Length: 95
Image 1: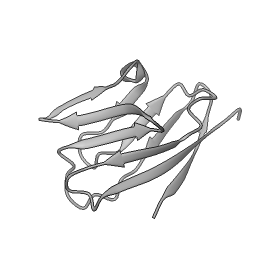
Image 2: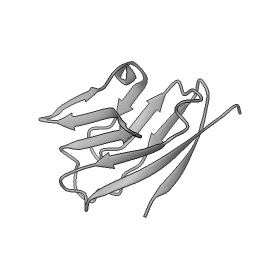
Image 3: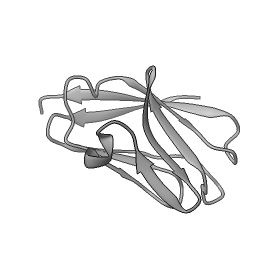
Image 4: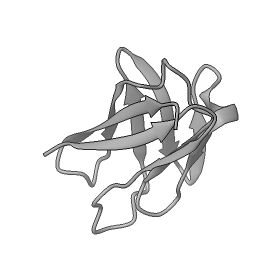
């Protein structure tokens, strides 16, 4: 199933992943774009998210930083160990 998260402009949020096994290769996406991607023990974001993201190196959980009105979108993660792919919805609020 999917999950929704509650965020706030200029705030932080984390997208927990039920990965029984340490996610070695994770890939987070946002709509028709790319957010972050973990592989070869190396984490890296896309576009300019790298300067506003904090992807974990264990469960593959992703922690965004400094949210905006555009951050309020349905994110989707992908992992080899994962069953297929999850969709963690993000909601940006004022407070």
